[PDB]
Length: 114
Length: 114
Image (cartoon, rainbow over the protein chains, first blue to last red):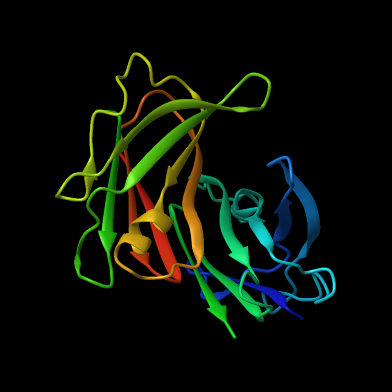
């Protein structure tokens, strides 16, 4: 599992469940190619997005559909979604955990690379 | 000043000075049209990006060139940049302050709408 996503809800103090996440890879022609997608589990985590074979160096964009999430909770969010753009494995493959902490008008995201 | 951006450095405890910011507006054909750009001042603030006349309803993307910033400090950042995507003025014009707090492997962004 070289790429894992974790999403938390700062309003309820719990994992953000069933959040849609879409991963894109920057294409040779500078366009974002769809790469992987899924929904966070009951623990707010999303595993098995790729394999180390498929996860080559490139620029990747993780897009978290935060708007849908809040709407479901009857809350009016500010952001269309949260995006995390980063260059991966440029210095060889690592294990990346992208964590996002969500609030209606704010979000933070941190990368734990190992 | 309907749109203001403020950036802080969490490693140095100071405003992030000379940070490039590019604002885009979602075009009719779903493409991002360049809308405004500038650099934060010595106070970590960017003013005068638009006028209320020009700042119409739409989906906007604020891109903060975090990578350049950290590179200049001789630090190797994780993110390519920080993006903030939101729908603006859908319910009439508001004043938007987008604040970003930066670290090499993490960033948070909050919106204060008045």
